[PDB]
Image: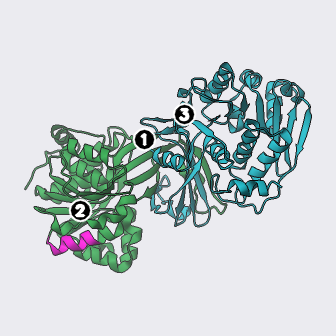
Chain colours: A cyan, B green
Amino acid sequence: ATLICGSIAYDNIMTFEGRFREHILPDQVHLINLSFLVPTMRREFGGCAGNIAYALNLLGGDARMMGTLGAVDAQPYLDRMDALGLSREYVRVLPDTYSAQAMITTDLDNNQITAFHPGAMMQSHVNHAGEAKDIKLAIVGPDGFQGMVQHTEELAQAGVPFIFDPGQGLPLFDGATLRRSIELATYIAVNDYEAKLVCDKTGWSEDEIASRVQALIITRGEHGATIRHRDGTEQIPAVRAERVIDPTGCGDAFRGGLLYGIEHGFDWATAGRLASLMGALKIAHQGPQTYAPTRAEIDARFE
Amino acid sequence: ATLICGSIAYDNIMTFEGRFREHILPDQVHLINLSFLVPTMRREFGGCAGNIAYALNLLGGDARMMGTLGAVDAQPYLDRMDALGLSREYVRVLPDTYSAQAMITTDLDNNQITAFHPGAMMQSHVNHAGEAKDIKLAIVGPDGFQGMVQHTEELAQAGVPFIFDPGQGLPLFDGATLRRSIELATYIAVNDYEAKLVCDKTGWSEDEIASRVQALIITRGEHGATIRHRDGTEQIPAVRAERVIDPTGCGDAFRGGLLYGIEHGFDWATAGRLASLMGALKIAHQGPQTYAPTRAEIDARFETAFGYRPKGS
């Protein structure tokens, strides 16, 4: 099985049928005390653990989420996991906390207010990667900082091969902990720019990073991807999209495709293309987890 | 007893370490993209019926909440009403629905933006206010619109005097329904900007509104309140808060006090003062229902602010 260590999040998408600006009051200190009804408040399913697990599930793989939700608002995702046949074993629900979530409100003129609450994601380290069962492969993506660090350590202790994917959590890393995570890692995935940040932060050249992992995966997105291994470098081409609707989640779809390749028999040339294709399949849809290709639709679109 | 019609909600209170006034200006033209971190979210018992009931209950009144909750998450609020000695006869719980959820963001100016996910509140008209027994007085506060209008008509038909408190529900009213609600109403409570809205929407002046009820009560935040009744106008002084912690529920705490004053035969000056005190007692604590003054404390604080002890006439 594949142990997907990452954050589990909701995006609450809210619409204000009105205009924010018409609600500043002319008080000595500008007053705003706006309340508005959101009867069609949307629940978008997110977080990288969720996104990748969803992508690995569609491929026919066996995905195991290790992430933390909040008891205040866990049920919807728990319900969704069960209906998708996803294991909830390593999904810990913590009391008196909210799940990781963004609140996104747009008015009629398309002005936006975004509040992110980290929530249950900041206590993801209560889930210990090593103390599991039947894991052949993992991934560590963006999560609460402590969780990310602990997972890398415990996955190595247990001897599990794992993709280190610091993602948007990369700015929290210093020279030393980034250097440490790379050595313990078996693979690493980043985009072209993050690869550059990693070089700049570690003080190691790309060559030096490569020698410390079985593969270094650099996604260029719309210009494709690259996979640097022992024998050399695969040049993964970009997959032609049906349409561009929402780029949000493509990276995680790409990873879902990638993790299927490693766990199964596929070489880096096929696995890299599998990844690429997953990124193109999600983009033609709104949200991270709305695209739902059947497996036969994936291998037909592969050839 | 006093029937408290209004929303029952869980408040989800977030802090913005900044000022909305710095990012939302009406003279500006660019697309707003305010993005911020909310390190803390506080879950609290809220909703206008809950808050007003809690306040009336603190004073020793008999508050009967009439509102709807959702089955998926009603339980802790029900357990709380039991613990508070608040009767649930008129609280109805609806299957396969969430209770109302307020997503409240507060900034360093104590300015607020609320996204209100009504859920079970949208079904609040499953309650019939005209069937409530032993009711001598009522408030109709912010709720699902259909429920608001229905409570209004039913309480009037049954001859129960009521305060019409449209509050955040006001944009849901058109002119004719607003006018009709006021005609049916015995008292109106609004804040100062809501009063202007009522005037603009009804086409009535504040003078004309006042003439159509026993009292028009207008709250002025930190400047206290105005009560326009048949025999003059009372200007209610603010109570300086012991400290300013959380404005959520201040208006409701005020309504709690006002309702107590009306039932125990307080004159408008004394009723408004008590209302104004409850507001200040509330603000010194986090959450709309965290404050728990004794009746003795309420009384001592009233005298300290106003110069006499509040008495029924």
- Disc 2 residue type? Ile
Disc 1 target residue: B42
Q: Residue at x 78, y 51 (%)?
A: A277
Mark nearer the viewer, 1 or 3: 3
Q: Chain of mark 2?
A: B
Towards the viewer: B189 or A18: A18
Residue A112 in percent (x, y) is at 60, 57
Q: Which residues are magenta?
A: B150-159
- Disc 1 residue type? Arg
Q: Quadrant of the N terminus of chain B?
A: bottom left
**Looking at the picture, do discs 1 and 2 lie on one chain?**
yes
Distance CA(mark 2)–CA(mark 3): 49 Å
Q: Chain of mark 1?
A: B
Disc 3 target residue: A90
Disc 2 target residue: B139
Q: Secondary structure at mark 3?
A: loop
Mark nearer the viewer, 2 or 3: 3
Q: Residue at x 17, y 75 (%)?
A: B157
Q: Are marks 2 and 3 in contact (CB under 8 Å)?
A: no
Residue B25 in percent (x, y) is at 58, 58
Q: Residue at x 19, y 62 (%)?
A: B138
Count neighbours of disc 1 (C-alpha within 10 A) and say few if under 14, some if 14 to 19, many if 20 or more.
some
When the figure is inspected, residue A67 is found, relative to residue B73, above or below; the finding is above
